[PDB]
Length: 165
Image (cartoon, rainbow, N blue to C red; front, side):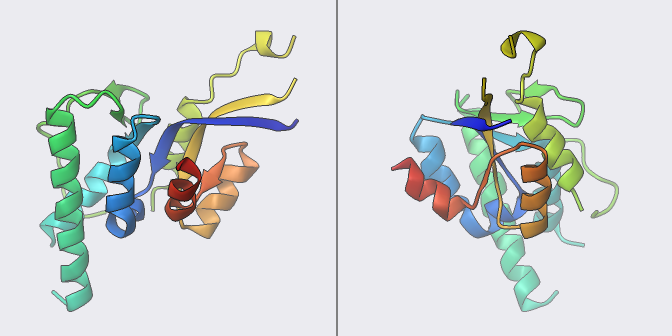
């Protein structure tokens, strides 16, 4: 089947935040899109922020801190275009106080499940191209593959931001 793609929900991965926070911020500011952050991503960010250190590690840790700060601020403000999704498929409107991992922890699975949550297919819709309103934002080539073979659209963040105007 062929896809008809109309971006609405955007699902980023951890490195999206580390590498591209400012762009994500811009995307959220646009108000055109719903940014849906897998809860595991936030957890991952929490872990990097905390730490368990070399230069690169320290650099990432700060980037991770900045990302959390961003998220917390936006959620606290009740930003209508920002959501978090649990592993179980629950949308969250607050992240105020998170359950932390015992220790620092590979999340394609869950990221993909997030994306797929917003693929709302019904027998009706086929009695035809496949409507898709979700896009995975990633630089990971393997993750990209997995998404594509699952009929989940993908862009890198730079590419997406550019497209978005």
